[PDB]
Image: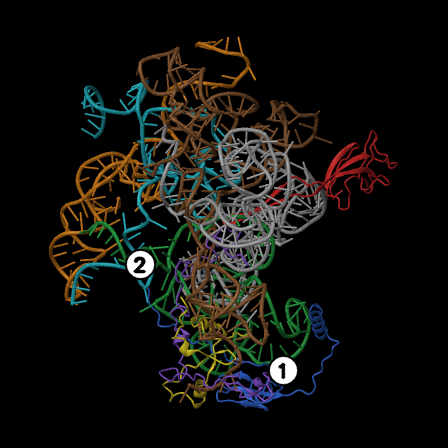
Chain colours: A purple, B yellow, C blue, D red, E brown, F green, I cyan, J orange
Amino acid sequence: RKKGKRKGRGHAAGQGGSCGFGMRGQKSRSGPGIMRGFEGGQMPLYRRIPKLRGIAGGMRAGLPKYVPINLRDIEVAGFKEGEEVSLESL
Amino acid sequence: YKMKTHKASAKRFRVTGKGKIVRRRAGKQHLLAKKNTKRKNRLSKLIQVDRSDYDNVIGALPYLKVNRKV
Amino acid sequence: HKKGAGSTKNGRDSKGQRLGVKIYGDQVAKPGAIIIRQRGTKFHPGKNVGIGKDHTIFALIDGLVKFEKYGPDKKKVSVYPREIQPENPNSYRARKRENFRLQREKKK
Amino acid sequence: IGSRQYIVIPGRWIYTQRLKGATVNDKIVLNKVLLVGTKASTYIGTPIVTNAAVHAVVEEQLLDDKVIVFKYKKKKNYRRNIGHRQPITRIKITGITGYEDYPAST
RNA sequence: AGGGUGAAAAGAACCCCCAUCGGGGAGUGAAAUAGAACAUGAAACCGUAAGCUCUCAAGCAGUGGGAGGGGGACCAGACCCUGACCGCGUGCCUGUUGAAGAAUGAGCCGGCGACUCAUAGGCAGUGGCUUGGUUAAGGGAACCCACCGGAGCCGUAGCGA
RNA sequence: ACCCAGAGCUAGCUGGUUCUCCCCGAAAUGCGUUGAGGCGCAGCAGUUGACUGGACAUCUAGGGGUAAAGCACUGUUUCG
RNA sequence: GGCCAGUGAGACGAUGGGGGAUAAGCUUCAUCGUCGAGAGGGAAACAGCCCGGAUCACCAGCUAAGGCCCCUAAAUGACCG
RNA sequence: CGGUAGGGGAGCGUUCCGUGUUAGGGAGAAACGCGUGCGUGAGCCGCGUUGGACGAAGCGGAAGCGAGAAUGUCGGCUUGA
RNA sequence: UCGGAGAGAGGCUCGGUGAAAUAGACAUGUCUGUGAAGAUGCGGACUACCUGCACCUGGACAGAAAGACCCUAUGAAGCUU
RNA sequence: UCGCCCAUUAAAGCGGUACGUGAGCUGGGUUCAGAACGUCGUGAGACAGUUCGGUCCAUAUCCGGUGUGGGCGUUAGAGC
């Protein structure tokens, strides 16, 4: 149990009177910050790069079928006449 | 309430098996005739996002399973 | 008293393109390492050394770079591998990296 | 004593720096006696007279009254208050052992 | 906006000042240094009394040195109050490249008066399990809570649109 | 117009943000920006892991066209 | 490389220059000092110059920069101009 | 071991809860005002007066938890006189 | 020009009642110097018993209204095509 | 303001003091709203272009000044 930062209660406790936000400006003010990923009016990365071939209008991503096991992974779970190694036993 | 994913960005950043963010290169949609055979091959392929901009990308979509190498 | 200031017709440039000698004389190189970005052939291509479309001069082989004298008032660039490169644990660098390593190991 | 001079006469006490290693009641001899005096006083050529050694007794090793050290700078929210009680020692002088050397005084 | 005499009105018979108000004795009561403006009663602000002390001074008012005087029914080179005269010493905050500033803010004193909570995501510290881990709603002589509920979730295979 | 409600509207703007000690300790730059007193990323703080050897000092080797100097080139210039 | 900040108005001085009138406590770059965020001593007072980097105590001592008639620590010191 | 923005570590108090219908308390608690104790500090600790019934530690927990600045705000009281 | 005299209502004194804006703290001199470049507060000088009342407004960048000019805000609102 | 001119005169000096002085005065000029002329503007409106009309606060705390008292001081106290 750490005991957190009740913030702005004397300059000895440290993070006091402005509370570790420096000096005015957008990040100082109360309320929401900005958009997250916002590059300041410069074109954001997330909107100046093309979008990943298949995911650009249709084409559902290759969601996996088959529930792959391996022969390496079976050997650890041992049974002599391994009676139907299937969806049931595993 | 429970974080919405930034599905504008998500569609430009995929994550690979080992856990690195990957993007497509910019440039090669049109005005292709005037570029070389050479540079279109470098613009075809995927690379990592630069270590600088990981912060914004991870911050945008928080259900990635992305490993900053630790 | 308050007269008008005449505009200029100047104020254009291009940010320095970063040409010049990337790999210096008597220095390590690689197969493929760019030695010089020069705008024309200030230096000329020597042996063991490619010369590109932009008069870019790059090394083909390992070895140290050499700026030879061409004949009548010009410069060449060739590359030569080096035979044997000896290291002695006598010296100060060797002493100190082993001392450091041993301290590292001693602590943990 | 603690790189610090004192006129010292017998049957009489002094305050000094806390003597490291000294007990509560424990007599000691001070061997740095730069001067002695009487009817016929006696200076020193070098330092210490020669074989003169003042004879004293430790009393107690209590701390000094609190001195308040206070760092302050104007307008920077830099008030820093800190006390300090220097440890001292009380010693009581029993006698001066006689000089037997270099008699001055005309 | 404006609560709290006392356990009990026992709320002051009588006397004095006196037209009233109010006051002092008396009386009641554990208490009236609880008297109705009544319980604890801080500060600013207003006085009264005692110790020292300013009318040739100049000063952000203190500070280091300390003349002369005074103590506390408790015998100290200890301690406290005053303070002749000397040296030093450009109120605080905000906010600036830079503020004693003649930049901003506060008449003073007391209260109230500001990074919180809910839910998620990342990271660290700690703990439990590691036969992988964990249950959600929901059920519980309610709420917590034994004890159930494995539905789901996370990890166990990537590559490619 | 007023009154009540949306409504604690929003305010990249100004003011304000309360106990103590110890350790480290910046920046006021580049880049982009309907941006210029804002923001992003880099640069420079703290903190915690991993990789190694440098730091300061002296001595060599490299390519430079600057101070200097010069009039063979490019201009400019005086006298015969 | 992980987690998590502030900063993004700078100022003066030395030098190398530009702009200006080789005016400005002017302005803009480049290299370094100090302030900024740094007390103390020298500069009468005096952010930015010189000396020097304040953990704390001492009614000890040696010195840097700078000084030695009095205000006010130290030579009304010396010899030659 | 100077330090603004700023980051990290270590603490003190405030009311309330568990322990606790604890001991301590009308031979005097909370409070209120004074201390020739203590601590690096926030603070702690004993005192007999006023006061008239609540309520320490220690080990733990939780917040309407610390004020001098907001032309803050409510109340009191000055100054000008 | 160029003022002068006089009457009322104040002003002044005594008794009665009794406000105000303002106000970090105020033991609140002049000169020149210094400094955020215009000092009762910093340096050097000069001048100056302590304290009322009447008159006067040069200063306290006096009081009054978070400049109404100027510019800024990817502020508000009217009006135009 | 400056300036020109009339009548003079010994002469009709030039400057600093927030281009001295608005908590001393004035409000003619210039920085609000009305209205007009010329002009610019498709228009609303505009123009150190012009014209007419248009609210100037204050009980002196301190320093500072002009006056005028009181206290105390001047070493025993007084009047000249």
Report whether E133 appears left or right of D28. left
Residue drawn at x 77%, y 32% is D12
Q: Amino acid at mark 1?
A: Asp
Q: Residue at x 54, y 84 (%)?
A: C34
Tell which subunit mark 1 falls on: C
SS state under label 1:
loop
Left or right: E100 in relation to A43: right
* Quadrant assignment, res D61: top right
State which quadrant residue A65 falls in. bottom left
The x and y percentages for residue B48 are 48, 79
Q: Which residue is mark 2?
A: C2
Q: Which dot marks residue C26?
A: 1
Residue D81: which disc?
Answer: none
Q: Is residue I71 toward the left or the right of residue F67 in the image?
A: left
Q: Quadrant where the C terminus of chain B lies?
A: bottom right
Q: Is residue F33 above or below residue I49?
A: below
